[PDB]
Amino acid sequence: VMDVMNRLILAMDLMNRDDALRVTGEVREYIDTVKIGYPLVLSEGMDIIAEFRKRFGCRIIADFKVADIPETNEKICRATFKAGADAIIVHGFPGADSVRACLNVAEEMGREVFLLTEMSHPGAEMFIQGAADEIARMGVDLGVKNYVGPSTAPERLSRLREIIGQDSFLISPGVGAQGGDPGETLRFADAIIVGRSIYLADNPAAAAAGIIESIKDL
Amino acid sequence: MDVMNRLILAMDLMNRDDALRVTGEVREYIDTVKIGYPLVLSEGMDIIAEFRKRFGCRIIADFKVADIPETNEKICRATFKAGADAIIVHGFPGADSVRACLNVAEEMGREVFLLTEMSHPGAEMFIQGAADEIARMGVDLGVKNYVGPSTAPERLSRLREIIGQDSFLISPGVGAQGGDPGETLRFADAIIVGRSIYLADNPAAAAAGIIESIKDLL
Ligand SMILES: O=c1cc(O)n([C@@H]2O[C@H](COP(=O)(O)O)[C@@H](O)[C@H]2O)c(=O)[nH]1
Ligand SMILES: O=c1cc(O)n([C@@H]2O[C@H](COP(=O)(O)O)[C@@H](O)[C@H]2O)c(=O)[nH]1
């Protein structure tokens, strides 16, 4: 599995290149893994991945929540890996063929798929929560090795870890701004994803250092 | 929304030259283009303004938005900043996530389309069982624009039943995936067509043919 420094992944959702670069640079000593999503990519272009690689010693996880038909998912993964992403996050709710499409491109291209089985926000309760156990098991059957699950529902994060087993890699958003606790989350997740707590802080570096101090024993 | 010839071009070519040439080749037949991540992640969001400059077409950004409310808001804002007239949003992540999109669309004078059900085989696993509830959620939220599958006309008909004749319904899965233009237009206001046109030896003839086959529905 990827070796995530300090078990901490920056969710860089600032939408301005200068600010994104400043904040990421400021926390570079604490984090070697950066999640880049559509807020930043749709604002600055896919070349932002190349710039982060150039500027920082950071792995890039493209948080694109890929959720189309198999043919389109393939194209999305190809474009994303071509741009230099190490990994891509894919939704499971569109079903097995759509996930396999992504797995096949990632295998061909030497990169990784993360499967999002369940989400951290209130709305996830309406439809996603009821499908989550089956989406996770589908992931296991398809040979998915990397997963995303919510820090805001520890009971459910724990179940997800059970389903995927200890060998699978699990990262978890919803820490800080959404109410998730770093320590409690790391009982089950390999790494926490943190965005606003860090990138909106007056001192992002102090914010990251503080999160890390709070989980030192882990 | 008044779509010329009830025909929306799914421009999923991933080269700017080809995308512009092929769209130019069929310009006389369409005034509405669906641009998705395959083109955008390959050529950048500036391509949307380029299409408006070259063709004057309306642009539907097919981004399958499927994140938490806070991120969805950012995605919609970036998308409408780029000149999209409309954006397509998944309903599966729940009501708060859709409302986030509705908020930005209202603020910038744009439209949200709710994807209630998909056209590919994997849609059967999780999406189909939630589809009617997602459609009702759309109605509850005041959504007026919907997307449903050509490949399952009985399910497309049910979606039309739920949302009423006043709602606007567009439908992909025509041609390449097996859907029939005329049958689809029994229920959808417009059909979405990608490969059958853009991979055609002669895209203009392809579009002309499709239109010929539905000429009594125009
Ligand atoms: O269930 C999920 C899945 C996510 O990817 N995310 C993403 O993780 C990040 C959370 O950022 P924040 O720490 O500011 O709440 C955002 O990029 C969001 O899009 C999430 O919040 N919940
Ligand atoms: O259920 C759906 C929803 C879609 O947006 N689409 C999209 O509609 C288009 C279908 O293109 P095609 O005619 O080449 O099958 C693609 O852009 C695809 O991503 C779909 O095929 N099925």
Image (cartoon, coloured by chain):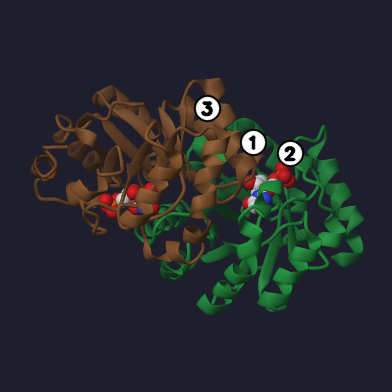
Chain colours: A brown, B green
Label 2 sits on residue = B198
Q: Look at 34% across and 26% down and name the residue there.
A: A2
Crowd rating for badge 1 (residues with CA inside 10 Å; few <14, some 14–19, many 20+): many
Q: Nearer the viewer, mark 3 or mark 2?
A: 3
Element at badge 3?
Answer: helix
* Residue type pointed to by label 1: Leu
Label 3 sits on residue = A106
Q: To which quarter of the image does residue A176 belong?
A: bottom left
* Residue type pointed to by label 3: Ala
Compared to residue A164, the image places residue B117 above or below, namely below
Q: Could you say where residue A162 lies in the image, as x and y percent from the top left?
A: 40, 44
Label 1 sits on residue = B13
Same chain, labels 2 and 1: yes
Along the line of sight, which residue is nearer the eye, A195 or A211?
A: A211
Q: To which quarter of the image does residue B113 belong?
A: bottom right
Q: Is mark 1 within 8 Å of ligand 2?
A: no
Q: Nearer the viewer, mark 3 or mark 1?
A: 3
Q: Are marks 3 and 2 in contact (CB under 8 Å)?
A: no
Q: Is residue A167 left or right of residue B157?
A: left
Q: Is mark 2 within 8 Å of ligand 2?
A: yes
Crowd rating for badge 3 (residues with CA inside 10 Å; few <14, some 14–19, many 20+): many
Element at badge 1?
Answer: loop
Q: Are marks 2 and 1 in contact (CB under 8 Å)?
A: yes
Structural distance between the alpha carbons of marks 3 and 2: 26 Å
* Residue type pointed to by label 2: Tyr
Q: Quadrant of the C terminus of chain B?
A: bottom right
